[PDB]
Length: 388
Image (cartoon, rainbow, N blue to C red; front, side, top):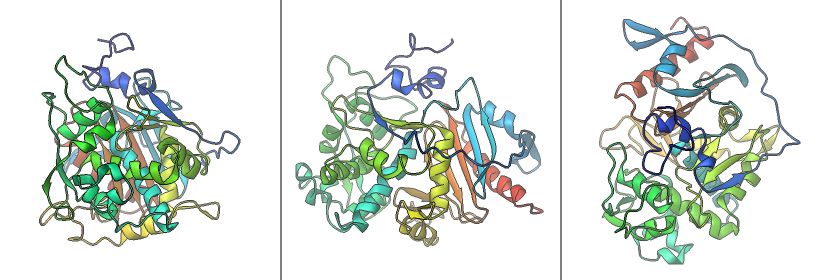
């Protein structure tokens, strides 16, 4: 089957092979709000190209496989490597157009996080206040009772009804956001959320806020609701004014929305790979672009100061999470954001490297995430001209 607009449906868009189309053409399938660049202030990426096609990736010790073929075998669509602020390697696969925005799943979350941090530092919000301080509609509900900081750190434990929907490759927290946004099928008896905020109102608390890490789209969606309420502007307009128009982006981005034109803050941003790399470089540079503080320097500072055992993702976990970012505690001090179907923004401050990885891998193997995580370290050490 060759996927196309004529055969991709609300039922199947997340499944192979349909996903290879849907995640490269989301705006042809859904409602969107544009995130504008500045067309008069694009900044071409300086380059220092190295062909990594035959770079030996260790699937495991003693089993190497060449990089370009490994990427393709795992349904990668785009792969961009930036080193010391220069483009080193980019590859686009499966007919995917480098200049067309791609789905990025949870990579969106870091944009909401960044704007929350900016607003907090502008003294417009207080991260230690409860969400229902700002969203009166959420008063005394589980997302309402959480502090902004708890939301930022994914420490709000919530379950939603299923409304009878289940898909074998989808967590309920994702299914519900998509049902809320009208991009999964609502059956004859559907009694579930009709817009994103409805989902938040259905939240049932399963542990006290702050008590443990629990990854939930709803936390980011709540934070985005705060952005909109405080600023009186859409999330798309906020991201455009604060970020997308400010760092030489080549193309517009866009957010998938619900039927009320509320953006999926947690999962709906679509952008080009080089543009995501520009944002990566911004964070590598602690929020500075051509001498201007675009985003708070605290974002990266605070992340880099998270020690093993602080903000852990579970008891004894070596991985931490802070302000919408994962902190693996790898040998590079890297930090990253991940998204379903093989998306990654990965920042390595030791090697001064950014990797953007976009995919449309409907059901990734259990091994590929660790293969990639280790491959990023090996790429960095290669670019740094280290013996290993």
